[PDB]
Length: 49
Length: 49
Image (cartoon, rainbow over all chains, first blue to last red; front, top):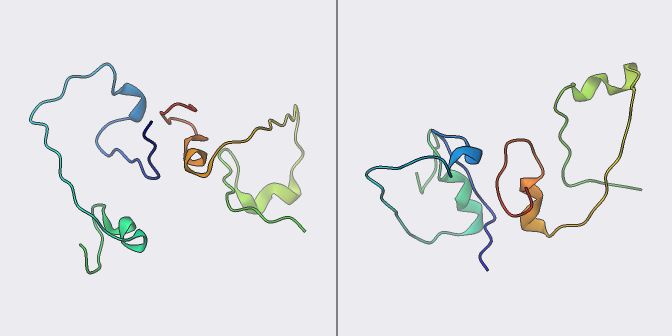
């Protein structure tokens, strides 16, 4: 059903998420416009960041 | 005539293609939707990969 236009993982490889166990898991949610999505990453400047 | 929205070379630099000779060349063709193009790359996960 659900498909994503952006997927990025930083401290782990994407092909090893099935063999791991995760601790202290949190999820954040909000809405922005298309041109502002690139700002959601470490070491970024701009209005959102 | 032809223009590409995506182009990414991996084991060679893009400015060296005109000076080399290539062996065992093969081409693969298929169709996906726009959101799935990002999965055509080494180390990716998803339904396509």
